[PDB]
Amino acid sequence: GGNVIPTPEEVATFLHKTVEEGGWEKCWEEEITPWDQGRATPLIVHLVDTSSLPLGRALVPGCGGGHDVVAMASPERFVVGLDISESALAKANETYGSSPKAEYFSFVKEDVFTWRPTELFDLIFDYVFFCAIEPEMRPAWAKSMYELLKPDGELITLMYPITDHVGGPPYKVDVSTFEEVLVPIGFKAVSVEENPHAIPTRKGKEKLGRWKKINL
Ligand SMILES: Nc1ncnc2c1ncn2[C@@H]1O[C@H](CSCC[C@H](N)C(=O)O)[C@@H](O)[C@H]1O
Ligand SMILES: [Cl-]
Image (tube, rainbow, N blue to C red; front, side, top):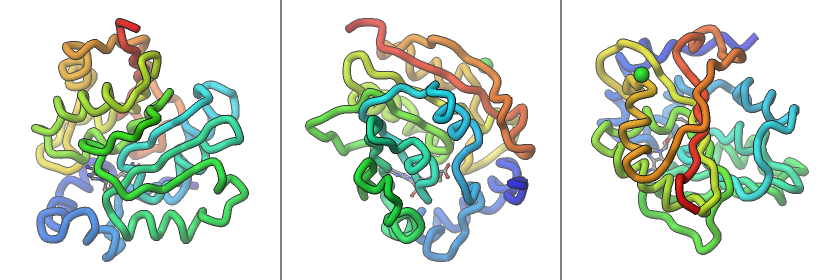
């Protein structure tokens, strides 16, 4: 029974007020976290349990409370959760840090736009991060996705929120918003599909995309 958080359209009316006052860290300190599902994203649980996510090294940018990081972690899928908020990662570690999966994941306080480890990622899963950033950061987001992926890596975007609302975060997006920043830098969409596991407040407001680099 997970229909307990506001629609993206409702979140967009107030979230900016705290982000503008004290950043994402203030949101986390004050428990103003209306994007947070309180559990792993149902689509992610489904894809993990049907072996429909690639194995290897995975990155979850703007991971927040880290639910999806932990759901994706396994002996063959090492997952890095990246967030700039100390309080977000404190909460993630408080919740999940003692999981037997702890040797297979790491919560790392780093900025997606600038952090570059020596070992890159087979997989990046972006959900509620592309829409969190200021709209003008979007071409830089695309270049960061390119740079953080190995040459045969895959970017998986749960593209959200596909809505008509004004303001943000979360800022409205559509498939063309992703295509416009990803294609010119050498990604190609493998497919774009509905998410039949969308929670009610997000049903019809998100689509799953898989992106690969056109040149190896
Ligand atoms: N440059 C950056 N690098 C890493 N994390 C960032 C960031 N800018 C914002 N964030 C983080 O992005 C998160 C957006 S909220 C979404 C959290 C998570 N994706 C979820 O679905 O629940 C916040 O936790 C915020 O601290
Ligand atoms: Cl579109």
